[PDB]
Image (cartoon, rainbow, N blue to C red; front, side, top):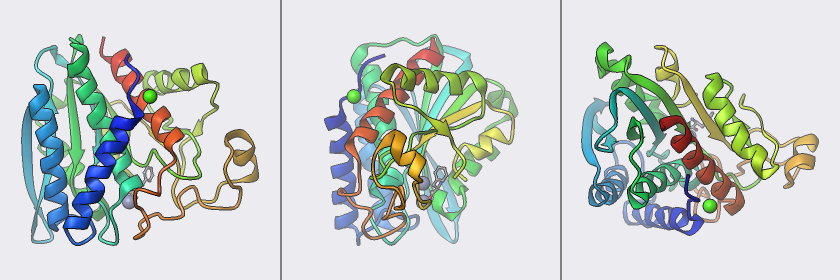
Amino acid sequence: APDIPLANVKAHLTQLSTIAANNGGNRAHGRPGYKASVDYVKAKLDAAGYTTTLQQFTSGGATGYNLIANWPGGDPNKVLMAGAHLDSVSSGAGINDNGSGSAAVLETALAVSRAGYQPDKHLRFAWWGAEELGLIGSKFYVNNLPSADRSKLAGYLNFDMIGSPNPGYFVYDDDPVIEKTFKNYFAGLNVPTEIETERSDHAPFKNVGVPVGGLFTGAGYTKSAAQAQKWGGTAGQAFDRCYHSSCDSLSNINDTALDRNSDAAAHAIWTLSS
Ligand SMILES: N[C@@H](Cc1ccccc1)C(=O)O
Ligand SMILES: [Ca+2]
Ligand SMILES: [Zn+2]
Ligand SMILES: [Zn+2]
C-alpha cells in the first residue's frame, strides 16, 4: 500500500473548515454546510474516475444525503467497503468529529486512482449523512440494500474520530481478520493499541452479519495514567476536550495520530482487497 500524504489530509480539513465558516459555522444535517461538504468530496471523486451516487432521504422534515463512490472493476460478488460520517453537530465545524475520518477515507480513495490499482475485490467508499441524529444515514443505506447485495459484502471498515489532540490508539474488536490487519500495521510502527470500548456507522452493518472493523482515538472519556505512559499526552484530561463543541476546529487535531490512522486505513484497504 502507498503512504498517505499527511499534508493532503490536512488540506481536505482546511476546505471543510472554510465550508463551515461560509455556512453559519457548522456542517449539520438540514443546514447548507452539510450539502456543501458533500459537493466538495463528490467533485474530487468524479475527477479521479469514480462512479458516484447521491442517495437521498428525509429525516425530521429535512432532506439528507449519503454519498456512495464505486471504483469501476473487481469481482462483483466480493465487495469491500470503507466509510465515515460527514455531518457535524450544529455547535461547530466538527473537524475531528468527523472531518478527520471523512478526509482519511477520501484521500485513500484518491490514492487508489493515483496508483493505478486494480483490486481483486470491487471497492466501494461511503460518506454518511445524519449520523448525529442516531445513525440515520447508514441505517437508511443498510435498510435499502437488497439482501442479494448484502451477501456480496466482504467487510465494512469505519473511521469516526481519528485525530484527537490527546490521543489513544483504539482498534475495534469485531471481525478477527479485519482486527488483525489493523493491529499488524501498528506493530510495525512499534505503537501499542487497546480494544475500542468508549455507537457509530458500523453498527447497522454488524447487526445484519457483515464483517466489520475500524479505528478510534478517543472522545469525552479521560486518558488514564497508564494510557499516558504508553502514548504520551496528558493523564487526567479528555482524549478530545472539544468534543461536540464550537472549539472542534482546525486547532483540534494531533497530526501524528491523523497521519498514522490515515496510513493504517490505506494498509487495510489494500490488504483486504487483493
Ligand atoms: N459516533 C460518535 C463518536 C464515536 C466514534 C467511534 C466510537 C464511539 C463513538 C459521534 O458521532 O460522536
Ligand atoms: Ca503518511
Ligand atoms: Zn462521530
Ligand atoms: Zn459526534
